[PDB]
Image 1 (tube, rainbow, N blue to C red):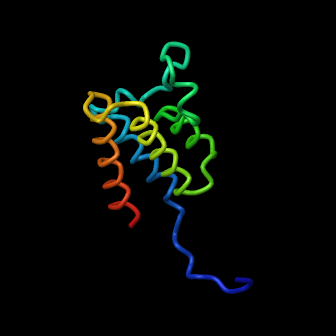
Image 2 (image 1 turned 45 degrees about the vertical axis):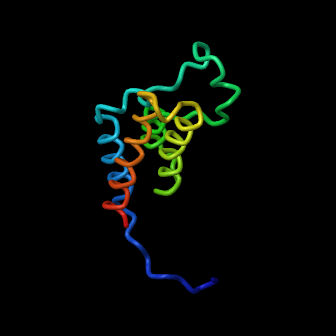
Length: 115
């Protein structure tokens, strides 16, 4: 509350560390369904169904241009990528499996880096 604060967590490296995690995501061999925005003109249903599209390149642009106020807003966009994937793809598909794999990969990096 007013003039009563928890000890200040060091957040000065957060931007650099999120960038490293994102680089590791970008270079994972199962990243290919998530590297670029889904083509809303060429993929029937996607625009109507997926209310907030997100992909790694859009996250990279947002990160590089100061559009994440903190590391949690960054994690929310990464998770959005895999939630979108689950909404539109069967679990038993290449893209469906890619999404599950990448989510697991991310959440371990996230825990190991910040928790």
